[PDB]
Image (cartoon, rainbow over all chains, first blue to last red; front, side, top):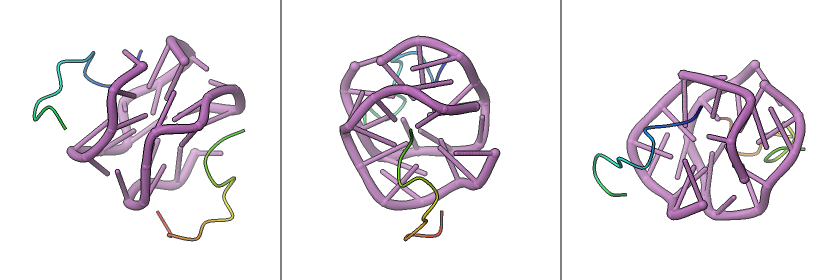
Amino acid sequence: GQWNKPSKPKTN
Amino acid sequence: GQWNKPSKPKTN
RNA sequence: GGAGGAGGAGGA
RNA sequence: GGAGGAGGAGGA
């Protein structure tokens, strides 16, 4: 139950 | 047991 | 560090 | 959402 489940939208 | 233990130096 | 999504700028 | 501290920009 976190952020976007390693599907990083801009890869950081 | 968190970040800066709300002695907040950067306001956030 | 997955117990929260308050948040994308850390990556687990 | 306090147990990670990889991070400081949420702030509870």
